[PDB]
Image (cartoon, coloured by chain):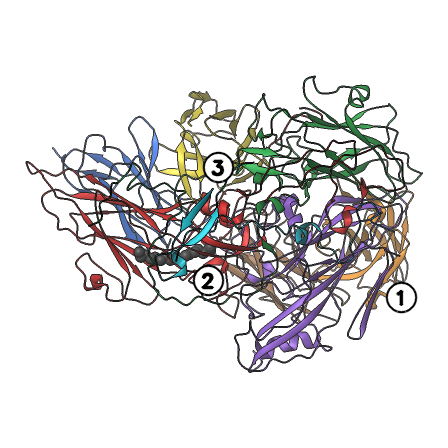
Amino acid sequence: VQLQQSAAELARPGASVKMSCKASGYTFTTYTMHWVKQRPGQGLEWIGYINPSSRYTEYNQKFKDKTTLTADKSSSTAYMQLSSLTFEDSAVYYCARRSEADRFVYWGQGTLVTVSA
Amino acid sequence: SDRVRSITLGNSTITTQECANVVVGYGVWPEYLKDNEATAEDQPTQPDVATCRFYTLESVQWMKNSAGWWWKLPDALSQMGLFGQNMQYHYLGRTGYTIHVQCNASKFHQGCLLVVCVPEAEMGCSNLNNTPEFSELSGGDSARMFTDTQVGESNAKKVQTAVWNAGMGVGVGNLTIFPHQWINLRTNNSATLVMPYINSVPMDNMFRHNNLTLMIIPFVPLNYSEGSSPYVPITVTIAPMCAEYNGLRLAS
Amino acid sequence: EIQLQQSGPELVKPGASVKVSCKASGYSFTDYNIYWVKQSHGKSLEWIGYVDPYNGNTNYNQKFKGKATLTVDKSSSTAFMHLNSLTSEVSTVYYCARGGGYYGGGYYGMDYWGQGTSVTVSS
Amino acid sequence: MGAQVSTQKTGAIHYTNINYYKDAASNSANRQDFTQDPGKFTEPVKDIMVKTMPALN
Amino acid sequence: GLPVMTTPGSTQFLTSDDFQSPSAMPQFDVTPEMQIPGRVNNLMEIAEVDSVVPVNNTEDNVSSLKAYQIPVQSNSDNGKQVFGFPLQPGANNVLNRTLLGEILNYYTHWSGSIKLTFMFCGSAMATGKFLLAYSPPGAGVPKNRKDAMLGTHVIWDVGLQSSCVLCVPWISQTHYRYVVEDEYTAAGYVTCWYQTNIVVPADVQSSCDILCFVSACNDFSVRMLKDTPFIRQDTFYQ
Amino acid sequence: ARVADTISSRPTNSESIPALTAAETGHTSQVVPSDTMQTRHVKNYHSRSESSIENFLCRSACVYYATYTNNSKKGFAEWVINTRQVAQLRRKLELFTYLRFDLELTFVITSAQQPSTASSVDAPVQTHQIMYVPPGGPVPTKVKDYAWQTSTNPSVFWTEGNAPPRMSIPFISIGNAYSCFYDGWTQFSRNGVYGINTLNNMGTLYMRHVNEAGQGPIKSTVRIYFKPKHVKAWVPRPPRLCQYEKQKNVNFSPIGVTTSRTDIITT
Amino acid sequence: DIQMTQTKSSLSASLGDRVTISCRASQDISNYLNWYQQKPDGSVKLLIYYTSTLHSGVPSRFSGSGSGTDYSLTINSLEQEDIATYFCQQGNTFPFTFGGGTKLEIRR
Amino acid sequence: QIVLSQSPAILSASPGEKVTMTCRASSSVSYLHWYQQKPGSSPKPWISATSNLASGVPARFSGSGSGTSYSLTISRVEAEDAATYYCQQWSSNPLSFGGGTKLELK
Ligand SMILES: CCCCCCCCCCCCCCCC(=O)O
């Protein structure tokens, strides 16, 4: 009934990185899958979502030119690719499943991304 | 022949030479309101030839990448002749309809349309918090069109026009439970639907309640080879049947 | 992809004629009309006319009824436009667009445009 | 003055009912009103078409 | 003081009992009835109406109108298969969400015959012949036209009448079958094959489409009402 | 409600074509399997008794539950009555456009003990009150309000440990049937709200502890159950595919028509 | 965007006391507020999914209030399992905006 | 013939505020579209049939209007939408363009 994410990842500035969030306990193609960013000195921040049935994605305006959301029905995971990484893009990224209209009931455990050299 | 009709209403006539039967409602024919079922006490007006006649709407083009169209039709005839003028001066009104959708092509074209008339079609909004505005739900005598993609949630007041959910959050193949016909270009040429008055009250205000919705959805897309005619239009004519009005006031 | 490739820039004399072309590719050519508009150097856009490539039927604006002639060529997917009796007001740029049906199919507008061809009269 | 509503649901005996309240919204559910009219959804068609005949003549 | 004796089952709330209860608003005058068209008396006349089935579930056609379109072409090899699915009307994801399969998911048992109508939505100058088969279980799914002609089949000749009905019969050991997928109450397979080719003239597209419809016969019946597995909730809708 | 039984069929060679029809007419085929193959005579004893509109709908379903706490001023619950906050009864009632039924209310009230600090808390049985306020009546703003006199508002008192309380409500409506869908507005200017919320004016339901708060707090929960009786239904309607999002409207996020398989020939 | 602001960012009280966290919106969000709790190991869970409606499995110490623009969250008896970070979230306008954190600690 | 009168001709706005850009017609119009032309290139097909954003248009832009009055709206004016916006009608009358409301940052 839980959501399971990947491990901590480290990339060079200018490179790319790909997370995952494997869903279990429910039917994966029924609910959208949202992604939230938390920089350690600030609060939570919404990025976007993907409809797993129709592969339709919608993004925030700040995160549109960098992030790329995708999914697959077979293994029932949801990926997220960050591109052109800077030092600002070092945070903890969660996956959440949204129920009803504005409520995230189930969250992931979060992956830590650090951008250094 | 079983493939010819002729429908006469007022000073207008519709002739067809390839057709299926006509579908009448839920089995019942449009009639007037009886004394057992009435509630309003003043006398209704019944013009019955100035309003009960065939009004033809705007034509739309069936393109190859088309998804569908819809009309509401107490609202589509709100500017049509003396039917639209009786709607303005009166507070109540009730009516049944007959709808004749017509689309012809040759023996070398292919395609299939579902012509369904649904009652009380609440459409859904793209933003999950609001309801759509009036101009997104209906235009007068002009079609509002479905899409083969999904409208984003950044659109505040817009109808969710993903065609496979029919705008109502439902299965589009299950829309054959309402009175419907098909226009198969292989066999058919037109579709005719006779609808009675369906509501939960004996009369209603015709400007803040659309109690019907006509949907035309291409289940099999239009296709032809190079050389054939690329322009195929779809035309809808609607005639009111047994219309009456109560509550005469100023013009609004 | 859908792309409307237009001709190149060219200079004419006052009173002379010019022939601009608009080659379209990536789609079935005779399914959509081809619209011709103009744009001056500091003014707004103005409509000239269109041509239906399936039967060669043209429909003109009243201001350009004698000075524009639209033809089509289905064998190479090219739509031409011949201009006649050019004056000093033809220091403009001409665009070609694509839309299907006049207003039966006006839901999409003219959704694929050309590059623009700049003509002028000079010495 | 209790009604012999007799026929019970059996496979292929009677039971007794008395109404105690003065309103008809107080009674039990109907549960035994078996009526069917499927032809208004499956044959909503003006000209009656016979099954063995061709539909388009 | 009449001597009584209370039995087990007293002061319990069973959610499917039939008792009388006192009215909260006495002598309330209800609104008189009206004649509204389209009165439904039984759920088995909703399930007897045709609805289009999505045979083309192919991982990007389900969020499209291409789920309902069965592709048919002018071939060059004989006896090719068109489609095929098991006859599980409430457990197989082809017939699961139709107007008949949505009613079966409120019940546990089902029994009766099933209609399958096929409409040829091609050009008017196209011909063709098909074989619409149904194989009872015990062997596998048929893999040839020769294996599938040995069961219940009909041969469809396309023409002026654009539709053909394959009526699968009730062949079962028990009187009822389970709506959920059970191996003891398996029902068989429905397949389609080319009998002859689709022959078209010049300047006609060689690729056509077929729509399929499903309904129930006049001996269909359901039993043991339950809750559907399709709707779900986490918090209150507000 | 016995179903029809099959008749014995013979080999045919004729010009009659029961299998060939035209689906473009909007009419479903009335064929039986004795027209397309050779059958035997069976006699069916099966019934369509459990699929009636009365048997499908007349079961109790939970529609809400509200909480309220003893040791608090303004500790009392309220609920504006509707049938659109739960997933299961909403989908059953929305297979039809218009409905007309009587109701049968049932309440299930429980309690729990809250962390006080006194030694030897010992409380008697609790008495509860559930008052119904029709639209326009005066509402309570606290627990010891004057509005709980119930001179004309119907209420019910109930002590813990007994059978659950139960009333019966007639067809209360302004119109001739309950409407599950409404394609229209409140105002004539076609501004403001839109949908089924324009017709929902059923009232409010209030809940409180009648007892005083003695020595430890008590948190009570009341569950509400609806049961339609004497049901009439008109204009059937396709069942809901997408999940519900809100209460007042039919908003949804789109979803595929079924789940997918790997082929068209795969079984 | 609707900016949610929690002006505290740190709060301290003893065990067994009543704490109050307040979140303020930019414009009217019309009772569409949610409260989340982030434990010190990183896990987030939903507490109150409206102005005042508790999610299932949440202890009854938690309580929500507010209307219009200003809202509140109350823990009427602070325990050791309630030392965490609390965020507010509006569900009225695209996109979803979360408030800043508010961390709890012990008074002495 | 239907003429389309746009207003204002010059709209100046600080980056990060909400602007409105209206158009009026002589009579009713079947379809109304919006285009954006930056100086030096061809006009791009933007918002079409008064609501539908084209592929690649940011979510800050919306369109509305019905009957005679139509309008285009930007919620937060970014620095890169400084262009001129034309408005075209597709009715039973031949064809018209608006007049080009120009936008320059303040
Ligand atoms: C013990 C006193 C309590 C009395 C409370 C009366 C409750 C009235 C309920 C109204 C029925 C609403 C029916 C739902 C309408 C629909 O189907 O949309």
- Badge 2 is on which residue? F198
Chain bearing tag 2 is: F
Relative to B215, say whether B224 is above or below. above
- In purple, which chain? B
The amino acid beneath tag 3 is Lys
- In brown, which chain? H
Relative placement, left or right, of F68 versus H25 is left
Q: Residue at x 88, y 63 (%)?
A: C67
Q: Nearer the viewer, residue E108 or F69?
A: E108
Disc 3/disc 1 C-alpha distance (Å): 77 Å
- Please check whether the numbered discs 1 and 2 fall on a single chain: no
- In orange, which chain? C
- Badge 1 is on which residue? C66
- In blue, which chain? G
The location of residue F48, given as percent across then percent down, is: 58, 42
Instruction: Identify the hue of chain F.
Output: red
